[PDB]
Image (cartoon, helix red, strand yellow):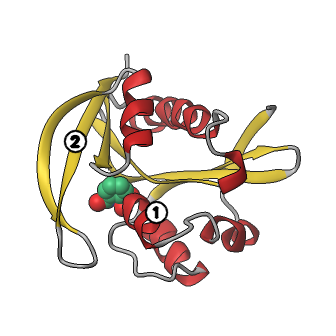
Amino acid sequence: MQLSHRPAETGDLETVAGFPQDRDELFYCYPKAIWPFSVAQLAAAIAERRGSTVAVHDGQVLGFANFYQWQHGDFCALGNMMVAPAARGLGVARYLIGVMENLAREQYKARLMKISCFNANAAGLLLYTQLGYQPRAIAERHDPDGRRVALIQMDKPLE
Ligand SMILES: NC(=O)c1ccccc1C(=O)O
C-alpha cells in the first residue's frame, strides 16, 4: 500500500460515487443523500463543503473525504468518508483521516476534529477509537425507513 493524496477533481466523481455499495453504506457516509448515489449529488456536497480530498494508490482513487463543518481556530468535522470496496481494511480511511487532521490544523488552525458515526457502522467506531477519537454524546437520527438510529459524536484534540 503506497498512498498519496490530492484535492478531488471532476474526473474522480464517477469513481467516488461508486464507493457506497447499498443504501446503508450511503446513509452512513452521507445521511442527507438519496439512494442511488450519483455524481450530481456528490458534486453538490463538494460545492457546499471544504477540503474534498482523494487518496490514491497504484494509480487508483481508493478513498474520499471532506469537511462538513469548519470553524477557524476551533474545529472541523469530517464527512463523506468513503473507500473503494476492494480497498477496505487496508488503511485507506486511516491514511485519509491523518491527512484531513493535518489539513484542519493547517487550513483552519483547528484544535479539535469532530467525527460523527452511525451506530451500525462498527468498523468506523472501532477505527476512530484506534485513532484516538473519544465518544462525547449520542444523538437521535432517523434512517431512510424512518427507523430511529444513534449518531455517536466523537472528537479528538489536534495540537
Ligand atoms: N453530516 C452528517 O450528518 C454526517 C453524519 C455521519 C456521517 C457522515 C456525515 C456527512 O454527511 O458527511
| Mark 1: amino acid | Glu
Decide which of tag 2 and tag 1 comes sooner along the chain: 1
Query: Label 1: which residue?
Result: 25
**Is 83 on the left or on the right of 25, as rendered?**
right
Q: Residue at label 2?
A: 153
| Closer to the camera in the image, 24 or 30 | 24
Compared with 60, 111 (above or below) is above
Q: Give neighbour class at mark 1: few <14, some 14-19, many 20+ (Cα, 10 Å).
A: some
**Residue that appears at 54% across and 29% down:** 98
Left or right placement of residue 107 versus residue 28 in this view? right
Q: Taking the image as four quarters, which one is ligand 1 found in?
A: bottom left
Pinpoint residue 9: horizontal percent, then vertical percent.
70, 64
Viewer-side label of 2, 1 = 1
Q: Please tell me whether residue 105 is drawn above or below residue 57 in the rendered image.
A: above
Q: Secondary structure at mark 1?
A: helix
Along the horizontal axis of the image, is 28 left or right of 11?
left
For label 2, the SS is strand
Q: Residue 4, percent across and down?
A: 75, 38
Q: Is residue 77 above or below residue 141?
A: above
In the image, farthest residue toward the top:
159
Residue type for callout 2:
Gln
Can residue 71 be seen by looking at this rendering? no
Q: Nearer the viewer, residue 109 or 125?
A: 125
- Label ID, residue 7: none
The N terminus sits in image quarter: top right
